[PDB]
Image (cartoon, rainbow, N blue to C red):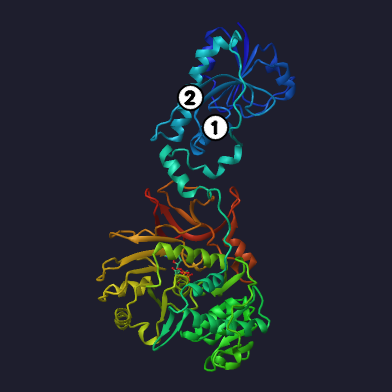
Amino acid sequence: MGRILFLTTFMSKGNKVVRYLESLHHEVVICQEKVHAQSANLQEIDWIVSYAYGYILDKEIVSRFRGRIINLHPSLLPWNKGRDPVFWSVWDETPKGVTIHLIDEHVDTGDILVQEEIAFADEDTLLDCYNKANQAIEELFIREWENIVHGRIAPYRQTAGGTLHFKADRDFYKNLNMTTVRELLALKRLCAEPKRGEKPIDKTFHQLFEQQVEMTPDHVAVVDRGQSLTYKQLNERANQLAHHLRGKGVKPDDQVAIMLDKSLDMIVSILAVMKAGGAYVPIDPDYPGERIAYMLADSSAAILLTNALHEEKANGACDIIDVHDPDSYSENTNNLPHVNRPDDLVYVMYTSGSTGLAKGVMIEHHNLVNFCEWYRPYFGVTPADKALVYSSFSFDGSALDIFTHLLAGAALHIVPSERKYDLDALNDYCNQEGITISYLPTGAAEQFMQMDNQSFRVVITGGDVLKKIERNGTYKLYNGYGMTECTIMVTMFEVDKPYANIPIGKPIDRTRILILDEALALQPIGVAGELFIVGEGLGRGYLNRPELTAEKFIVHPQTGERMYRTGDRARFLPDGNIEFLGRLD
Ligand SMILES: Nc1ncnc2c1ncn2[C@@H]1O[C@H](COP(=O)(O)CP(=O)(O)OP(=O)(O)O)[C@@H](O)[C@H]1O
Ligand SMILES: CC(C)C(=O)C(=O)O
């Protein structure tokens, strides 16, 4: 009949298409490589049929064979042009079908000959989809071939729009081939990029705090033993000190060290540093003098807010400002002119030097603002609540204590030394004062479940594996995961039942968790892998450690996004909650 060139790389040589064409007495030449005009495979060729051909025909060839190049593309063109059509058909959630079209001067854009719809079952695998489509289009070709040879089909131009994909676009999804349709789309919801319409955070913390002061100025803000400050009182005193600081040269991104024991002066100092424009570097005064001397040096802190008691532990490291000297406070009680942006430093905390020397973790305002903006509505915090300043102010767990509740109008209650380790005593305080919400490390939180409590409405815990769930009170328990580098915490779970492994929940606001293999490629739901963090949580990095910063804050090779690699193992559950599975090594 005629000699037909059959171009293809992925399909076999005994296709139902080739056999059918052969059955009509056509000599079918099978070529699976790029060719040129001189190729002996283009000799006496009546028709060219391409089917999953991974190369481009030269324009010289397309011109000579105009109207005689027929392509089998398993998609509903213009949807899913290019490579991996069936896969992106499912992922991008586009219309589905198979198209037999003419080949023109571009990628899968030529006019259509025949096209029909196709359906994939929710429980079909992507491989099943790939095969169901290849079989459908092969049958369509056999059915409509005669109509195409006699050129009685009027080719119609493709609808406007569609999508296009390239060979490498599927690299990130290389492990999803044996996944189910609905199992794949589930993974899409959990890990797909942010939706449209989002705007960057436009507020700093002290900006929002000054707002909260105007709303609840006379409400109690912080308590320590018998003494207390209201939102206005606290705000005015912090301004007085902030004015003095900014007058001593404090500028945005400057680090100011604070060295105090838990007290009202600590809260004033922290805010005062913020309002002045700097970022506070907390230094526990009980730390060994070695750590203190090193923290003060590695940090660029030119100023140190401290007592006269702990003044000598600096060994003259920097300019001292006595929080108890009236000369350290200005007359001006008014808020200062704003000079910060959400991407300015807000605080710098050092991780315990378990491995190697301690590193200074930088955190920006937008990092802290996002956490508090999520914390308030998630736990329904109102000015009626009262929370504990439990954790050492050198740990990011203290940021949860102080900063979240202050923006909700609640009241902070400083936890002194005598009721830090003695949790039974701390329990009585909570019932006395009516403490309603606080965060307790996994350890202390587990012991506190023994005590009888009627005050707490909610308690949050995290930092280690939360094995024990039984507790006497009536309050909700929450498990939270995260590290200092991504601001306090990134996921939250409400503990409703007991669990063998207790999940760490779903991501907070404007954060995304990805479970990746050793090649940084997505892992299907239920498969373990290194947990990666993306979004508003990621801080600036490690202070004066750019090489180490780049090691942990990566630019992904495929999606090009900035992610923090935790070094933790985890796996998604079918209901969206995350399961922690210990460290990597
Ligand atoms: N709810 C949780 N369950 C289990 N592991 C958790 C967890 N929350 C956090 N983790 C893990 O345990 C660590 C606790 O946080 P960080 O104290 O900031 C790290 P570190 O200071 O290097 O060591 P450390 O955990 O020995 O204190 C996190 O880095 C994380 O890997
Ligand atoms: C201190 C709190 C926020 C914590 O879970 C952590 O840092 O791991």
Badge 1 crowding class, 10 Å Cα cut-off, few under 14, some 14 to 19, many 20 or more, is many
Q: Which mark is residue 151?
A: none
Sequence order check, earlier mark of 1 and 2: 1
Q: Looking at the image, in which quadrant does ligand 1 appear?
A: bottom left
Say if 220 sits above or below 502 in the image.
below
Q: Are marks 1 and 2 in contact (CB under 8 Å)?
A: no
Q: How many marks?
A: 2
Quarter of the figure with residue 269 = bottom right
Q: Nearer the viewer, residue 373 or 139?
A: 373
Badge 2 crowding class, 10 Å Cα cut-off, few under 14, some 14 to 19, many 20 or more, is few
Amino acid carrying label 1: it is Pro
Q: Nearer the viewer, residue 45 or 317?
A: 317
Q: Where, quadrant-wise, is the N terminus in this rendering?
A: top right
Q: Which mark is residue 85?
A: 1
Query: Would you say 579 lies left or right of 357 here?
Result: left
Q: Nearer the viewer, residue 259 or 526?
A: 259
Quarter of the figure with residue 171 = top right
- For the question of whether residue 6 can be seen, the reply is no
Quarter of the figure with residue 424 = bottom left
Q: Which type of secondary structure does the marked residue at label 2 adopt?
A: strand
Q: Which type of secondary structure does the marked residue at label 1 adopt?
A: helix
Which marked residue is nearer to the observer: mark 1 or mark 2?
Answer: 2
Say if 523 sits above or below 479 in the image.
above
User: What residue is drawn where x is 32% and y is 69%?
Assistant: 457
**Distance from the alpha carbon under mark 1 to that under mark 2:** 14 Å
- Residue 190 image point, x, y percent: 46, 49
Q: Which residue is tagged 2?
A: 117
- For the question of whether residue 488 can be seen, the reply is yes
- Residue 49 image point, x, y percent: 60, 18
